[PDB]
Amino acid sequence: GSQELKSEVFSLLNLDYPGLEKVKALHQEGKDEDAAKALLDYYRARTNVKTPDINLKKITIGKEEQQWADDGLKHTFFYNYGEDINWQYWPVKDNELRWQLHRHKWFTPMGKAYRVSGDEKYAKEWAYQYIDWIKKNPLVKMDKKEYELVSDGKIKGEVENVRFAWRPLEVSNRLQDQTTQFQLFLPSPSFTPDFLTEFLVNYHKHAVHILANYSDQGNHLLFEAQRMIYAGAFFPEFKEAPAWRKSGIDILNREVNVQVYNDGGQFELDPHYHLAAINIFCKALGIADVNGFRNEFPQEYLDTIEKMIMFYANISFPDYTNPCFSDAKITEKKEMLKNYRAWSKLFPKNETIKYLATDGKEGALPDYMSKGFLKSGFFVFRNSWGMDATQMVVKAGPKGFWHCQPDNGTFEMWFNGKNLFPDSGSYVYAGEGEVMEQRNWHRQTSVHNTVTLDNKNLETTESVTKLWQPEGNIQTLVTENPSYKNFKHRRSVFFVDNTYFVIVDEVSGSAKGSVNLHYQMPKGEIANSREDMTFLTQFEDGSNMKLQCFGPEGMSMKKEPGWCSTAYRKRYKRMNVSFNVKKDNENAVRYITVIYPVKKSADAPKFDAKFKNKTFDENGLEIEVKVNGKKQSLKYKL
Ligand SMILES: [Mg+2]
């Protein structure tokens, strides 16, 4: 091949590393060819270095992955880039295509294809393309005053190429992925000693480049730091490897303290972005942990990640799905089981992560049921952790950012296997034009389970928790949001007898207009009575509910088409119901809503509800509800 003995590799290595004794001896004598041979011997016999990305005892290849691998064999890269590979090949002006090419997305497919098929064509070809990329993509620099005077050509093109081949985004991707390529191809005779020295010199150059080019902020900085830990954990024989690990750890530790509330919730208030953050922080912890470097992480980092996991476990439903608040789609059970299995290896003394990883075969659930997160603004009522549970998750928190929607007070509710109050969801993640109109539709306050004034989006999103009482046969949340100028919305949620919910909405202030109490119904056949202000699902036996709203004289009800989305660019029709009251003076507007889950619709009880205090009380509430004629008082003092 075109690989050559890069004897400068030996100066990059800690030649006192255990197992490198013959490398060190040969290098000291100037026998660098024999030293390179001994170095390959060392890596082939190594031993205490693995990655979570691959199990060399369980290598598989997918159908598209075999397809990318076979294309790679013919220089088609996941276009045909020629026999003499044109790494700058531009058929049309496409910067995105040029950057994507330098991710080498087909190298690892060829590795897997090499191991599963067992024939050297994949390893031969990859060695060639690996070296050829090194040769045709040098990392160079030029003065800007000279760059402007140079004309187009090989020297100018090489300098401009650096913007594409060595952008930190792609460089850090290769830092991680090449640990997979290394493990897959190392047994091959094409993986010669000279090639090894080329691989390590190139790899080291990538790590040094990232250290010099860390992003200022964002998820990109997290991935750079995580992959610097990859570099230093997978090649701890580099002199600089402990420094690379420490660099990445310090960054991740600092950023998790900026991003995560003390109760464990990530500050975007978005379950999907919360889970993505867990996984960045755990992938870093995992590569270190499996290679003996767990102790390099500060204890506060371990504790914070464990709190993020417990936060996610709490706001999830017993079927492992998450509420679709903010921009969150549903992450399904198969993916979450894989997540809990990985997390349980990282926190093996956490008995709840173990329970969730094993679906209850081992481990233990927490010694609590309902649970509140007072900094993040998420509140969970539950009568069980299992598939028979009744569970509500209420979102009523501080201001968020891009993903968070104006939905303070909204909730999802899940009963005995089915989500009966799903969020309208995200639907459109990003776009322009008509799709942007649909993204904003789903962000409206009026397409959530909360209160609006004239159906307007909340002007302020900054909930205050007045009371949180998670224990007993009456559990209570009281939250208040100054939703509009001269308008305060106090929502009281009672979870009664571990069975049903009573939601009291009280709007105070001098603001006038139409007060709208919105509920977004589940999909399917739902019976309603305008006379009684009742809604009763007509679903298959197992998970049903009855909702009834009790309001002042003259309350009206309106049903409009609405939408629910659990996956991006997919949505289904369901009813958007509002209970509307004309607020034409300074008196408060007050509602009581009963929500009662039942397995069979025919068993849904009759309700009544009344305020005992006929005037709004800034410092308390007392109501009386009836269930099949049986009285229950619900009250609190603030
Ligand atoms: Mg929403």
Image: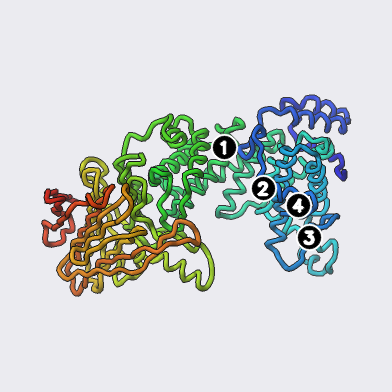
Q: Which residue is mark 2?
A: 63
On the picture, is 207 further left or further right than 307?
Answer: right
Q: Which mark is residue 602?
A: none
Q: Secondary structure at mark 4?
A: helix
Nearer the observer, disc 2 or disc 4? 2
Residue 35: quadrant of the picture: top right
Residue at 78 percent of width and 45 percent of height: 126
Residue at 44 percent of width and 43 percent of height: 308
On the picture, is 280 further left or further right than 86?
Answer: left
Disc 3 or 1, which lies upstream in sequence?
A: 3
Residue at 78 percent of width and 60 percent of height: 88
Label 3 packing within 10 angstroms: few (<14), some (14-19), many (20+): some
Q: Which residue is mark 3?
A: 88
Distance between mark 3 and mark 1 Cα atoms: 36 Å
Q: Which residue is mark 1?
A: 286
Q: Nearer the viewer, residue 560 or 505?
A: 560
Q: Are marks 4 and 1 in contact (CB under 8 Å)?
A: no
Label 4 packing within 10 angstroms: few (<14), some (14-19), many (20+): some
Residue 51 in percent (x, y) is at: 63, 36
Residue 430 in percent (x, y) is at: 52, 64
Q: How many marks?
A: 4
- Disc 1 under 8 Å from ligand 1? The reply is no
Q: Which residue is mark 4?
A: 71
For the residue marked with disc 2, what is the amino acid?
Lys
Q: Secondary structure at mark 1?
A: helix
Disc 2 or 4, which lies upstream in sequence?
A: 2
For the residue marked with disc 4, what is the amino acid?
Asp
